[PDB]
């Protein structure tokens, strides 16, 4: 009642899992992924101009 | 009827008995058929058999024993079947018997 | 200010401004744990024959 996976994490892939247990029917599913912006723990330095 | 062809749909964990059985009773007149099955290894679901004439009369059957063999007394005969009673997901629940 | 950060980006990421987007990259997979419902599978005799 709790499966697990790991799909290709580029956007532009249909993940899908056809997992069913005994007596539950064959649980097909189709997940997709969209954008995942990186943005690390950044600290600004100098505010340079003329 | 004859040809006691049992179609055990699911071999459950399991809980309250429930599980798949289906006597493909090669019968000419469906009706009230003898249901309660001649084997204590798995507890039967129902008691009478709604006999589909030449039909898979469905039935419940619950056994918790993972090496199950269900030998029913489908009124005009016995009926042989064996399916692995595959163990369930949860841990604690209302009831079960097999 | 020469070649762009996202524009000269390797790893195929969409780079972009202040909410500093580096997204849809060609990097990493998606792990997942799916606590499936009871209602997601059909019945045991609930299926068509």
Image: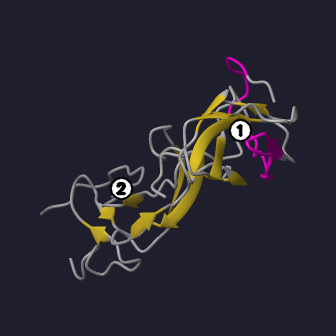
Residue tagged by mark 1?
B88
Quadrant where the image shows the N terminus of chain A:
top right
Residue tagged by mark 2?
A39
x 64%, y 33%: residue: B18
- Our reading of the magenta stretch's main secondary structure is loop
Quadrant where the image shows the C terminus of chain A:
bottom left
B85 relative to A33, above or below:
above
Q: Nearer the viewer, residue B74 or A15?
A: B74
Q: Disc 2 vs disc 1: Cβ atoms closer than 8 Å? A: no
Left or right of B60: which side holds A46? left
Residue C41 placement (x, y as % from top left): 49, 47
Residue A30 placement (x, y as % from top left): 39, 60
x 66%, y 45%: residue: B21
Instruction: Tell me which chain the residue with mark 2 is part of.
Output: A
Q: Considering the numbered disc 1 on the image, is that residue within a helix, a strand or a loop?
A: loop
Q: Nearer the viewer, residue B97 or B45?
A: B45
Q: Nearer the viewer, residue B67 or A41?
A: B67
Magenta-tinted stretch: B70-95
Q: How many marks?
A: 2
Residue A10 seen in render? yes
Asked if the stretch drawn in magenta spans residue B46, the answer is: no
């Amino acid at each position: 009642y709790e499966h697990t996976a790991t799909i290709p994490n580029v956007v532009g892939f249909p993940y899908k899992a056809h997992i069913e247990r005994n007596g539950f029917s064959p649980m097909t599913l189709q997940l997709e992924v969209v954008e995942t912006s990186w943005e690390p723990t950044l600290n600004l330095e100098y505010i340079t101009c003329e | 009827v004859t040809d006691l062809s049992c179609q055990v749909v699911v071999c459950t964990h399991s809980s309250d008995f429930g599980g798949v059985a289906t006597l493909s009773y090669k019968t000419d007149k469906p009706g009230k058929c003898a249901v309660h099955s001649h084997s204590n290894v798995a507890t039967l679901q129902e008691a009478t058999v709604d006999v589909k004439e030449d039909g898979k009369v469905t039935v419940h059957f619950s056994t918790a024993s993972a090496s199950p063999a269900f030998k029913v007394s489908v009124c005009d005969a016995k009926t042989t079947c064996t399916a692995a009673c595959e163990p369930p997901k949860d841990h604690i629940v209302p009831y079960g018997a097999s | 200010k020469g070649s762009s950060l996202n524009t000269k980006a390797p790893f195929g990421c969409k780079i972009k401004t202040n909410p500093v987007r580096a997204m849809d990259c060609a990097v990493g997979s998606i792990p997942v744990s799916m606590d499936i419902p009871d209602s997601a599978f059909t019945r045991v005799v609930d299926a068509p024959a």
